[PDB]
Image (cartoon, rainbow, N blue to C red):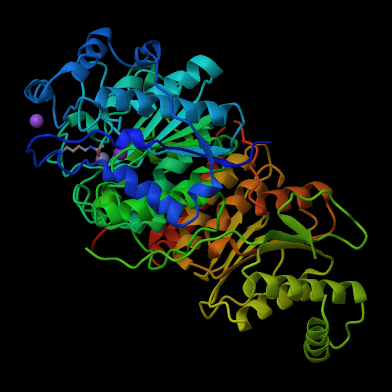
Length: 638
Ligand SMILES: CC(=O)NCCCCN
Ligand SMILES: [K+]
Ligand SMILES: [K+]
Ligand code: NA
Ligand SMILES: [Zn+2]
């Protein structure tokens, strides 16, 4: 199984720049690359990546996406003087040429292809290419918007040709529309393109009618182009995460790509002069994290734009941190998307409702500048500690470890002699020492991040885990419970949110999300739909300090548990304690595997039950006034 993250970079791509006055182009500078790599070096991230050399894209590789006439014309720019380079540049929109830019464009393209090969040959899990010039605006026969050749379009076409891939997802979180990518694949259903972008009702460059939400692709490609226009500046973390939970992710997990390519422009970050958005660099840690369960983690991140040298370095670092599996930073202050974003979100969901299962219920009435410096991120010495039943030894990943001090044993006796007088079952009393011992390593030590304990008696286990977390203190605790019945969990004072997956149904508490999913073959689609559209929005807004997972022994869990514990590690810096009632070798191994940051096997294929969709939207109705990140329509004003 693949391990490690590639970092592809070369100083040569910094050796072309603008040679005449042009305020439109002067923001695209060599230092974008140098500042980004040096930021990775400063924080020790570059040294943890597998360096892979750049190469030149060949002529034949360039012809995958560009015309012979355009290549031939660009191939002549190395021989041009300054006056001739200016005249050549003025044939195109917002792009400049330089004696060395043709060379650098072939390197940017070759670097991208190197990244695709390293990931697809399983030599690395994932990676990032820091390249200049950017690519996503370039077109079959035109340079455009600082881009000469379309690096990310190359990558998808190359992955199709050489690895026979049938489904590729391109995520373009740059603040500009990648119209070159859209045109490239607009008729191709094998490539799903998603783009958000500053649009302002077509008044923002590149001012194209087809960058609007109504361009869904053409022909056999209808539905595989998703545009989410931002019609006001100042979009925040909440807007970006609402886009992901309510548009991108439901479509991505349904599509089930075999490879993910990110057009990663960080001009969507606070401080950027082109974007004027307000999302913090930390959000890219989560945008990366939320996509990593796709395609068994095979993700190729390719630099596009980003022009505030400081937000640029910090957002690059947050992305590589997540590629390396480091714990995600906590995002505070999340809430409803703004009205203009909710309007863009409802509009794209409505037009896409003809093509995607997650949105299908919408089609019928019956169903319907300064910001703080990012904190340090670093992997735990031992990421995951495990406490199997006594005697059971397992083959653990190299970053896991098996489980009991005297300090702890006195605490268990104190807890026993106060709250469980009649308790003598020394197997339960063992698990209490394990829970307290594991939690203390999780909360106190930076050396342990999360853990999993097998228990026998849920009530005493859950009470001791929760109460020990709440007095540490962990300001807030998110409980995720798979099972029926009521637990010793009080959700009245706002310190606990309880997500419960059951079979019965329910309650009026707004600190509680109960999901009664009908048994059958459609539960996997239903669970994933609840996870992305309900569980994750609430969990993100709640912002817990610890996540407590609980699985009843009586409980189609194996198919989705791994996706949940991977995605839920976006909360609480990955600090999750899972209690498994009873020994199940497979469930315990999958839990440890996902907690430790291993790749998750893809879901494959379908469509969920209408009764389940109805049940889920009733929950959204009931909760979205308190938890606004749940909202995916504009609220009705009085
Ligand atoms: C790569 C990129 O972000 N290009 C933006 C072009 C701006 C034109 N005003
Ligand atoms: K974009
Ligand atoms: K397409
Ligand atoms: Na110009
Ligand atoms: Zn851009």
